[PDB]
Image (cartoon, rainbow, N blue to C red):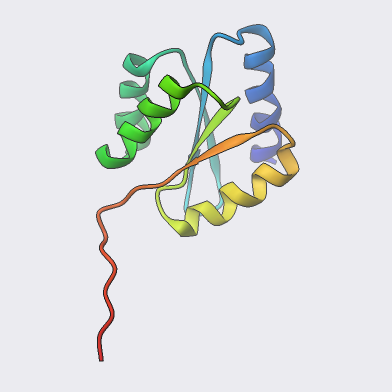
Length: 109
């Protein structure tokens, strides 16, 4: 399936170019997208291509500046993170899980 081939290609990009970076987009339908990226200026293309929130986008740019992981997952909601956390187990390579949205928590009676 679509999420099997890209999971290998993320490692293949890094095997040939370890100086380059990988972005992964969570879709709410359970689909996935793979993107190639080199610098924060390149991530600005992904922001408008994938439709990432600007509060999330700064976390992607910061994750490149830290540079500690082999690929990056955009868990825009915890409903998307449900796939991101479970993929990290089967993938064996380490993944950083990026969170951020405009919704605020409350309790009422």
